[PDB]
Length: 19
RNA sequence: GCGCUGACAAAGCGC
Image (cartoon, rainbow, N blue to C red):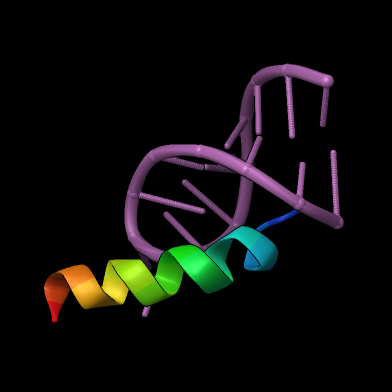
């Protein structure tokens, strides 16, 4: 199951929204 | 395993 593969790219953006 | 929601979760739900 693709948890980490999706997460990696989504994470960068998710963080950068809050930032 | 790859998406897709979610906490950048776990879990779910497609392919």
